Image 1: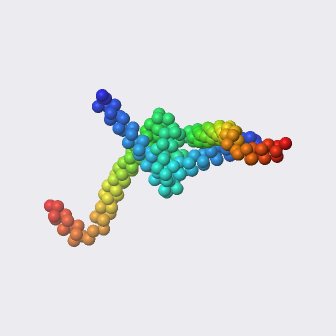
Image 2: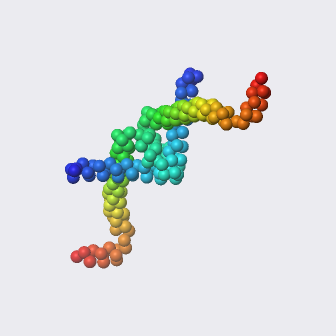
Image 3: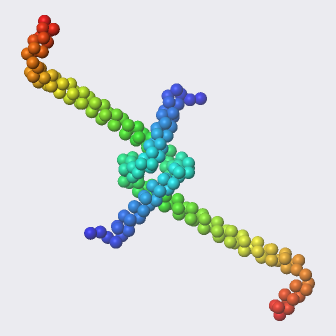
Length: 103
Length: 103
């Protein structure tokens, strides 16, 4: 399956990663996370994260917005179809009265 | 002092950075930070952070350990000096009795 080494390295990676998460967790409940993050990340890496959060918002707002559009269209067409069927179901009296308020 | 642009870019950088900190803050009080961090950072960047936390521990344990050493030495010498002076202050009776338990 896997070497005795690669497995120890995999395990170490995981522990070290967990430890970072916990370090940052704790720093939060202490108001030290701004200092810690300055220690853990260069200025360019922080900018990069700041940039990535903005990218995520743009991707999300983009998709949200395409979705609201596709749903508007969907609903606009469904309403025409549904209007059509309901028109066929209307009683003659309603149909003629409607026809008559048209003419 | 500074261009109207560079100032707007400086301000944007700062806001985006603050927003990341808050995003990660909130994800913590929600148990989503493992997912978010996976979204915000590649596998190589996480390894890198895991590595950096380990480097910080090694640098700290290193310095701690040099400090305990310098303090041990310090204290070892201060004790000899202090033993010396106290020996000069001892009463003859104590000095001779000590001398006598030596011989």
